[PDB]
Amino acid sequence: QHQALVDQLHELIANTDLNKLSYLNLDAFQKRDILAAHYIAKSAIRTKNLDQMTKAKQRLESIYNSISNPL
């Protein structure tokens, strides 16, 4: 479970690289949300905090889905 979650997080982090999301015209608040989630995700992974890893996974999944799809 731990490794599966780390892998999911790393995939989500890779898929939410701000440079690669330029074409989506994200608002500054969305960029900041992504930057914060990346910091939290990395920090949670490094410390093996499963609850915070779960939080960050749900957050990044939600963001990636919403920015990729109709308002």
Image: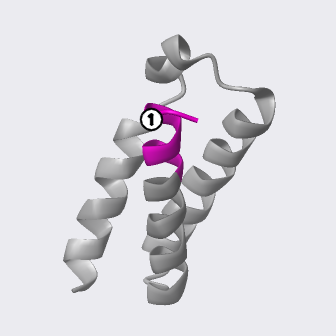
The magenta-colored residue range is 63-71
Direction from residue 4 to residue 46 in the image, left or right:
right
Q: Amino acid at mark 1?
A: Asn
Q: How many marks?
A: 1
Q: Is residue 5 above or below residue 26?
A: below
The quadrant in which the C terminus is found is top right
Q: Position of residue 57 (x, y in %)?
A: 44, 66
Q: Main secondary structure of the magenta part?
A: helix
Query: Which residue does the image show at 36% across and 38% down from the upper left?
Result: 15
* Residue receiving disc 1: 69
Instruction: Work out which quarter of the rendered image holds the N terminus and state it.
Output: bottom left
Residue projecting furthest to the top: 23
Residue 50 sits in quarter: bottom left
Residue 24: give x, y in percent of width and height.
54, 19
Furthest residue toward front: 70
Q: Residue at x 65, y 25 (%)?
A: 26
Spot occupied by residue 53 in the image (x, y as percentages of width and height): 47, 75
Task: Please tell me whether residue 36 belongs to the stretch shown in magenta.
Answer: no
Q: In the image, residue 37 lies at what x, y percent?
A: 60, 55
Residue extending furthest toward the right: 29
